[PDB]
Length: 198
Image 1 (tube, rainbow, N blue to C red):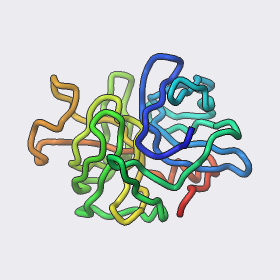
Image 2: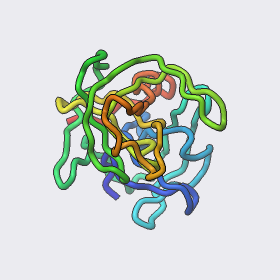
Image 3: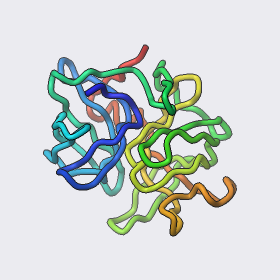
Image 4: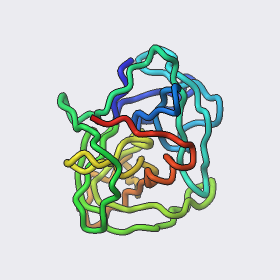
């Protein structure tokens, strides 16, 4: 499969999440994603095929993971936006007030602005600290997906949102949304990953 930020993958033939970013660790290929999406050694699949397994994760506390892929997978410096692509040019962390977009298999590609950093989300499993909050909308399934500026700078991966009864927060005004992502830089240093860019 071609690995592109934003696409759907399954975990153990059951939950869905979205790909965050292509990374390497030496010779191993992988993608970063949200830790609550799977547990270590869970099987990830894209388009019915096994692409790799969860290698490490931390959730709750933090919410991050990376999946090691087989050699057959094709890592790409891209995040999906409808039928088009956003190129990943780097990981400069943007500041509050910066405009930001995100990609995921449930709501697609949505943009908004970073509204706050170092937020705590209290999920059923326990607290997750140090998250950044933006007001681009998102829905269940978008977890794990890319947050990236239009300019190609990767910000992090989708953690959670204030879900409404329709399964997303796209029906309430941006003032009211709290969509949160896990910053990318700590995930990349923690596992010694290098981001694939173009």
